[PDB]
Image (cartoon, rainbow, N blue to C red; front, side, top):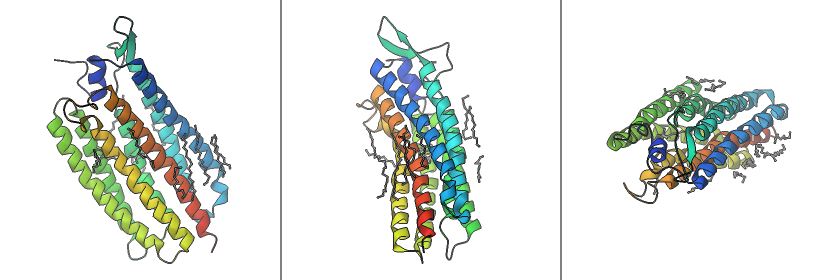
Length: 271
Ligand SMILES: *C/C=C(C)/C=C/C=C(C)/C=C/C1=C(C)CCCC1(C)C
């Protein structure tokens, strides 16, 4: 039995095969880029709040708060990665360090728990609904989004120990994800009514961005099993891939999403 690498697939690899210098350093630098971009975004959203009418500024405020939480928690995740493995001169690879704290997904999942409700909420300060009620949409978003992250978090505890449960819990989580997609699509359709064609075009881009960037997360969750129980991805390569797809998803769903909403708000105050 491999006691030290039971908690997650990153630990499992690091306690059996170990990581190449390339995989270790690559992952270290990708995660560093992750939190560095959130700090830049924090400054962008603060400095541009004066460019939008007061009625839309709650969206820029919620983007700045998402940036603070993501900078701090991705910074923690980055330090956790680099401090958890150490180099063995004999084998020439990085292995899980029993004296360290071991790699822990808690930082990222906590970041999601906080940010998902705010990302979904903030669009309701830019578009107008038509036949739907603000409170009803808000409550559906907050409930479904919380459940999606919780059931997902439960799933990842069984990643190494019980793949069957890993997949069943991820399927449950996917149910909530599809309900979010259904609600967001109705919101975008109602928000397109009555606004200018320029604004409708930006909203269409927001919808495509939202759909792709959020679908990246379940992809990264499954990444090391996407080539079978002993394929190319069941390895340090599935780890590099998973961590890269999370970082791309985070920049897109938090920073780029917020920039587009700010551009929509500016467009709206032109008619
Ligand atoms: C800024 C962080 C964001 C927007 C996080 C989004 C997270 C998700 C869409 C997570 C989705 C999941 C599934 C649909 C199934 C597998 C488990 C999750 C939690 C990764």
